[PDB]
Image (cartoon, rainbow, N blue to C red):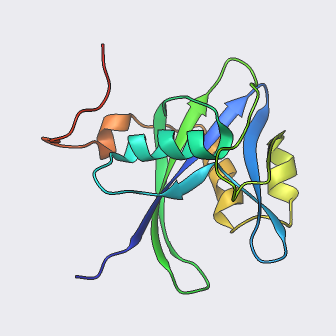
Amino acid sequence: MFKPHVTVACVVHAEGKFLVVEETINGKALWNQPAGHLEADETLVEAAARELWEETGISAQPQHFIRMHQWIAPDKTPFLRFLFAIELEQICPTQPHDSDIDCCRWVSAEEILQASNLRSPLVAESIRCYQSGQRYPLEMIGDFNWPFTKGVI
């Protein structure tokens, strides 16, 4: 029963800008994609939608799967990190609902690529991947005979 830490992230893109959330780790203001831990009884995409809401008050469904990164953090924590893409027709207001989050900012790709205050190296990596331009359907990591309810219409 080895079990990894499973997380989801969102690359949220609007007019040449990527949504980043700021957070103080221990003493330091760091940037990340809107992300978090997968929960019980929840679908990956539902995780991602939730996390997006909690950290940014933005309420939007993920559009495409981009990729998953398997990595160990330097505290030695094992993650499987699933990265999604959400395109929006325009930038929108943000307000976090999760006190972990100090503020949100919309920033350019170069501003994330060049930055030194990133939560972890995968923050940068997610942009490279997104910029590559290859996207994948959501069903490809989809639930199967799932017992609980999901969306509607």
Seen in the image, is 1 located left or right of residue 93? left
Q: Residue at x 38, y 74 (%)?
A: 4
Task: Please tell me whether residue 11 is drawn above or below residue 38 in the rendered image.
Answer: above
- x and y, in percent, of residue 62 in the image: 49, 34
- x and y, in percent, of residue 45 in the image: 40, 41
Seen in the image, is 32 located left or right of residue 10? right
Residue 132 found in image quarter: top right
Q: Residue at x 84, y 41 (%)?
A: 108
Q: Nearer the viewer, residue 127 or 52?
A: 52
Q: Residue at x 68, y 68 (%)?
A: 120
Seen in the image, is 127 located left or right of residue 1? right
Q: Which residue appears farthest toward the top when viewing the image?
A: 153
- x and y, in percent, of residue 135 in the image: 49, 37
Q: Residue at x 12, y 41 (%)?
A: 145
Q: Nearer the viewer, residue 28 or 89?
A: 28
- Quadrant assignment for the N terminus: bottom left
- Quadrant assignment for the C terminus: top left
Question: How many numbered circles are shown?
Answer: 0
Seen in the image, is 114 located left or right of residue 130? right
Task: Please tell me whether residue 115 is drawn above or below residue 47 in the rendered image.
Answer: below
Task: Please tell me whether residue 29 is drawn above or below residue 57 in the rendered image.
Answer: below
- x and y, in percent, of residue 113 in the image: 80, 55
